[PDB]
Amino acid sequence: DDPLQQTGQLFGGLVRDIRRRYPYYLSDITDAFSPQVLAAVIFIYFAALSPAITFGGLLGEKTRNQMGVSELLISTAVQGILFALLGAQPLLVVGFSGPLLVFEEAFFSFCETNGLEYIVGRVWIGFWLILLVVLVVAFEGSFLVRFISRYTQEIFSFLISLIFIYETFSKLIKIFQDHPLQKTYNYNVLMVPKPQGPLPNTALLSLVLMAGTFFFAMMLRKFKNSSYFPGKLRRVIGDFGVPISILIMVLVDFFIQDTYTQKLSVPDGFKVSNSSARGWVIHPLGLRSEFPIWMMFASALPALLVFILIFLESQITTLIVSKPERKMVKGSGFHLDLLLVVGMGGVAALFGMPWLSATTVRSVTHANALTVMGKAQIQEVKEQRISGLLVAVLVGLSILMEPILSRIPLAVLFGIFLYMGVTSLSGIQLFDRILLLFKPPKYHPDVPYVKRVKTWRMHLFTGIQIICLAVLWVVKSTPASLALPFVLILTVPLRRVLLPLIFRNVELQCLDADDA
Amino acid sequence: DDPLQQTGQLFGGLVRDIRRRYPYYLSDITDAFSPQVLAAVIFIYFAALSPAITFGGLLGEKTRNQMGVSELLISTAVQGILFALLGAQPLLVVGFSGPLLVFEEAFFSFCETNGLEYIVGRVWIGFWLILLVVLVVAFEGSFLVRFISRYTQEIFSFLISLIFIYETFSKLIKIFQDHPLQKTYNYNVLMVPKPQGPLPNTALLSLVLMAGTFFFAMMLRKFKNSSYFPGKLRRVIGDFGVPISILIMVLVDFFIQDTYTQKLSVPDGFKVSNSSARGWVIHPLGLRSEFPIWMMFASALPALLVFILIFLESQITTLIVSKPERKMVKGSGFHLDLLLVVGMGGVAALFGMPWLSATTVRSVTHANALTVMGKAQIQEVKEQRISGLLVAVLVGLSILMEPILSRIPLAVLFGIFLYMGVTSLSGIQLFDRILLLFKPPKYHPDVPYVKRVKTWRMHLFTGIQIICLAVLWVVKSTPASLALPFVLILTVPLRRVLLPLIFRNVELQCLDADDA
Ligand SMILES: CCCCCCCCCCCCCCCCCC(=O)OC[C@H](COP(=O)([O-])OCC[N+](C)(C)C)OC(=O)CCCCCCCCCCCCCCCCC
Ligand SMILES: CCCCCCCCCCCCCCCCCC(=O)OC[C@H](COP(=O)([O-])OCC[N+](C)(C)C)OC(=O)CCCCCCCCCCCCCCCCC
Ligand SMILES: *[C@@H]1O[C@H](CO)[C@@H](O[C@@H]2O[C@H](CO)[C@@H](O)[C@H](O)[C@H]2NC(C)=O)[C@H](O)[C@H]1NC(C)=O
Ligand SMILES: *[C@@H]1O[C@H](CO)[C@@H](O[C@@H]2O[C@H](CO)[C@@H](O)[C@H](O)[C@H]2NC(C)=O)[C@H](O)[C@H]1NC(C)=O
Ligand SMILES: CC(C)CCC[C@@H](C)[C@H]1CC[C@H]2[C@@H]3CC=C4C[C@@H](O)CC[C@]4(C)[C@H]3CC[C@]12C
Ligand SMILES: CC(C)CCC[C@@H](C)[C@H]1CC[C@H]2[C@@H]3CC=C4C[C@@H](O)CC[C@]4(C)[C@H]3CC[C@]12C
Ligand SMILES: CC(C)CCC[C@@H](C)[C@H]1CC[C@H]2[C@@H]3CC=C4C[C@@H](O)CC[C@]4(C)[C@H]3CC[C@]12C
Ligand SMILES: CC(C)CCC[C@@H](C)[C@H]1CC[C@H]2[C@@H]3CC=C4C[C@@H](O)CC[C@]4(C)[C@H]3CC[C@]12C
Ligand SMILES: CC(C)CCC[C@@H](C)[C@H]1CC[C@H]2[C@@H]3CC=C4C[C@@H](O)CC[C@]4(C)[C@H]3CC[C@]12C
Ligand SMILES: CC(C)CCC[C@@H](C)[C@H]1CC[C@H]2[C@@H]3CC=C4C[C@@H](O)CC[C@]4(C)[C@H]3CC[C@]12C
Ligand SMILES: CC(C)CCC[C@@H](C)[C@H]1CC[C@H]2[C@@H]3CC=C4C[C@@H](O)CC[C@]4(C)[C@H]3CC[C@]12C
């Protein structure tokens, strides 16, 4: 009955994952039929787009425009549409992440030094990723996800949610750095590619738009589970909380004529960036020069790292999204979701388009957007394939809707990314126990991990996860940021060796409960 | 036992009000001995000062600097110190208001037209106010305050609290009007008396500082009756909520070097503004020219209006402050508080210094600052004379502490005035019933005015007060703003004639309850 279990046959998991979810494919399509879903499409679109614009820029400037915005938008769309209509957990938002950006930057520096064609080099990384995932799905290597306890999920879920907030602020800090509050400004300033000199009222209006969008979003979330207005209208106005928050603040910026703000820049059309270097289809043997033999066999060793990055990235997100406390009746297919994400990424490499992973904050936010509330607890979750599809489609059609996106500020969306960061710490027992460090022992939740276990022991456990978070934060900040998945895997030994010595088995049953 | 009752003897109320409160004068002084009180002194100081700076400016520019900041600061201090050590309800904050400003502007225009000495003219207004209050206190004319039902108190309390918020925003709107968000600015701009041309980052930083101070104050108020940190520390950090909110935001502005913000401007020393025209002591018969006879008898007719303005201003504030739902054990003396406020104002006129009234928002905020909370409901109220004294003293010594006040922005204090406006709508059944218009009939407080009385009837009553508010708002906006007290008195006939026809006696007992 459980999804994580080793079957005798080869490709046994993939078969059982299909026969589980595909009978509900009609019901899935019809689960989209509600206003929450439309509000979820509109919300998660900007959550899906803005990274594909941001990382698209970061790839472009870094990798001499071999991978850019045009490539990443098309990649995120095609892989998003395929995964929405096939993937066993459609709530998983397939997009490009920080850990993947770091690899492309690292692999480019490696290709640049040795004297190799980068875009061609990636094709052979992809060829191994097609072999390595099919090898794992054959023997059901996703059975290792069984041993990823709440411990590892909570640390990852919290680490990523904290980093996502630190990301959102550093963008705002960069505006104040580029556009400082000076006494005097250069009045005649070009903004052809971007403001050259500092501008007046740009950094503060950015701070205003961010603070405003975050406020409206958080106050309309409060309004949803309030007791004001009819229950029919209240939930509709609440579900369209972020859509209204963006609409208000985009119009606030629209009526401000003279003062400048940074807005969503998309490509002219659907052209590969730097057409002089590469086309659409990347020739494995080489575009210009003869790509050598030793790399075509030694493309496994980078692909092995890329696999671990995506595998730990995607499958831990699947546990967090398809958690028993979240009312997920349809199910979750770990073998099939791994096959598509990594498989399509390997095929995407052939077209010089970035491989993607199930992004945690985007996926959790997508589930949280489609989760209902009553009385408070979860009744069901609106689990469809159309929200996953429409988001991917709109990210594909993003360039054709440049005139609409051109009027939307970034400072507005930074308010929404702050919301996505705050909101993602909802059902995280770790974060809940960080709050209980500051609460005195009189005011506690009255739940097994505080009642069964002593306050001294509970804070010691909570204390180790802070030590564990602190290590993982240092690992990212240091040059070895691609090793963070291997340091996150090392949290499982900790739970299954070190803690059982220091702690009793009765307490870990409650502290690190498989289900709340 | 009740304070509002007509005794046989002359000056009967004044005697009974003294014999009530003065036995607790030792206990009053010792009721100051707590951290809430220090936090209340610091909070209400800026609430007391900034109007005496603002109206001080408005008097100065209007009345050719005959009344100014120097006059109003000294007047607010001396009358504040005397009232703190004598006044039967020390929580009443004696200061200058909008209605009094409008009269001084109107009386100056009258004096200017006819050809009379204004500052001399006020002395004879004051001479009548000394006679007219002592005549009222003799016959116990404060017995008319008995008939001011919750109806009239709630409308006034809400009208004044709404106007105080509209006041706070219009100041912020004036900054954006004077310092607009333009593409280009004049770089070389003098600020000798004040910024001549528009400045960059002034209006938005003002909006930031206001939004920030309001946020910190409202979040530290939430923290006070939260369940985080020790109960000993939590209430102390909470009680010093506004002091911390100002300290944070004043330091935020301090570390911003180059960009300009408007700060608390106080006089050079203790010198009367426009010394050429007037001295300290105003000669009744005239300073320069012969002040005529007809005015010395016809100074009653303006003084009669000034009396009604202060009498309705002060005594309705006394009902709101000394309300039965607020745990006021010490008592409240309506006859003695009327005598001091109007009497000292009449004596203050002799020194060319403005007469004052018990200001509603400042008084309510002062009581709310000294009110404790448990579990939520009120246990007791820290009712002392030292908070009233220290505020008055600090407003007196404000000019000697110019270097401290010079670094404090106005935009910061606008955040605190927004807090004072929001916070003042706490125990107002009217405002509570405005919220119940938007709530559906399932989610209601379960209290006599919603349970005994039907929702149709309850919203009709709530509806009349909105019609009543709308009239009182139009009355202020129109030139006849000094008639608003007489239109507020007209709400008592409404309750005792019109409503008893349209409504049943059983419903008014609950809707318009003397006590909750
Ligand atoms: C419980 C939590 C508490 C914390 C809550 C904090 C929430 C954060 C909210 C942030 C504010 C969002 C609104 C931004 C508005 C910016 C307006 C602007 O820059 O336009 C200038 C506008 C833009 O129009 P313009 O540039 O065409 O101006 C042309 C003017 N002439 C021709 C004269 C040059 O310029 C003006 O100054 C026009 C004159 C009118 C003045 C307009 C200013 C309005 C400001 C009101 C703010 C109201 C909200 C404040 C709430 C804060 C406290 C809760
Ligand atoms: C509920 C949601 C709504 C709540 C709203 C509450 C209000 C929030 C804002 C309050 C804080 C205001 C800080 C003003 C910063 C002014 C800029 C400054 O320091 O000068 C730049 C200074 C200029 O001053 P300078 O001259 O001393 O600096 C040196 C200048 N250079 C570099 C050229 C040599 O420039 C910098 O050096 C950049 C440093 C980065 C500082 C940026 C701080 C950003 C503030 C973020 C606050 C978080 C709030 C986010 C909103 C959501 C709520 C969490
Ligand atoms: C676009 O691609 C071209 C072609 O590779 C890049 O040009 C190379 O990179 C830099 C020039 O910027 C030189 O060091 C190399 O010698 C160039 N080689 C070739 C084959 O031209 C260029 O960097 C890319 N431009 C961007 C940033 O889009
Ligand atoms: C001080 O007060 C005097 C008295 O009004 C002001 O001097 C007058 O200015 C008005 C215009 O506002 C003229 O109509 C009068 O003729 C002036 N009277 C005189 C000569 O005193 C003065 O403007 C005020 N300002 C100062 C100097 O402090
Ligand atoms: C482009 C950016 C700035 C904002 C875009 C958000 C737009 C598309 C959102 C914001 C509010 C939304 C509306 C909110 C409520 C409803 C009622 C529902 O019964 C039908 C959809 C409808 C009518 C929504 C349509 C989409 C909507 C207009
Ligand atoms: C996306 C691409 C690159 C993936 C390629 C992997 C191939 C080898 C996979 C994908 C789907 C798989 C099939 C899915 C289902 C079944 C039914 C089962 O009873 C026997 C195996 C069989 C027939 C699988 C064989 C292997 C298979 C064909
Ligand atoms: C339309 C919905 C369903 C899918 C969203 C993505 C669409 C718009 C994207 C994905 C890949 C894109 C194609 C990629 C490459 C090219 C070659 C170029 O020389 C012309 C445009 C063309 C032919 C693009 C057309 C639009 C396209 C099909
Ligand atoms: C991040 C680095 C610098 C610090 C490591 C995390 C800190 C915050 C952790 C590590 C050990 C923890 C302590 C371990 C045990 C106890 C006893 C308990 O009865 C109260 C909490 C208290 C006192 C914990 C507070 C938080 C703590 C101090
Ligand atoms: C800061 C400017 C704007 C106004 C002046 C406010 C000053 C005097 C306020 C702000 C914060 C206050 C402190 C806050 C908390 C405490 C703890 C309490 O157990 C003793 C008093 C003490 C130590 C306060 C002393 C006075 C204080 C320092
Ligand atoms: C701390 C409490 C008791 C007092 C607060 C207010 C004090 C400081 C103020 C109120 C009125 C003030 C006086 C008003 C008028 C004058 C005349 C002037 O030519 C010299 C200063 C002098 C003599 C002032 C001295 C200080 C004073 C007495
Ligand atoms: C804004 C100023 C100028 C006047 C407007 C007053 C409005 C808000 C008042 C006046 C009378 C009121 C109505 C009186 C009675 C009822 C019946 C009740 O079952 C539903 C609410 C309803 C329908 C009220 C809604 C609010 C109402 C319409």
Image (cartoon, coloured by chain):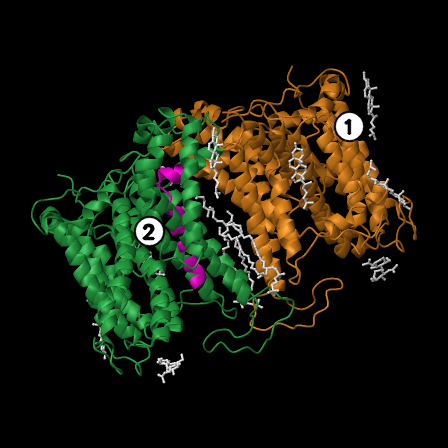
Chain colours: A orange, B green
- Residue under label 1: A85
Residue B394 visible within the image: no
Secondary structure beneath dot 2 equals: helix
Residue B249 position, x and y percent, is: 43, 59
Q: Nearer the viewer, residue B491 or A457?
A: B491
Mark 2 residue type: Phe
- Write down the residue under mark 2: B486
From what the image shows, is residue A251 above or below residue B116? above
Q: Residue furthest left?
A: B9
The front one of A444 and A482 is A444
B245 in magenta: no
Q: Quadrant of the C terminus of chain B?
A: top left
Prevailing SS of the magenta stretch: helix
> How many callouts does the rendering have?
2
Q: Quadrant of ligand 4?
A: bottom left
Q: Can marks 1 and 2 be said to lie on one chain?
A: no
Nearer-the-camera pick, B328 or A470: B328
Residue A353 visible to the viewer: yes
In which quadrant of the rendered view does residue B111 lie? bottom left
Residue range highlighted in magenta:
B410-432
Q: Position of residue A198 (x, y in %)?
A: 64, 67
- Circle 1 residues within 10 Å: few <14, some 14–19, many ≥20: some
Q: Is mark 2 within 8 Å of ligand 11?
A: no
* Pointer 1 residue Cβ closer than 8 Å to ligand 7: no
Pick out the residue farthest to the front. B294
- Quadrant containing the N terminus of chain B is top left
Question: Percent x, y for residue A130?
Answer: 81, 33
Q: Amino acid at mark 1?
A: Leu
Residue A166 falls left or right of residue B123:
right
The foreground one among B92 and A287 is B92
The answer to whether A16 is drawn above or below residue B161 in the figure is above
**What residue is drawn where x is 60% and y is 31%?**
A320
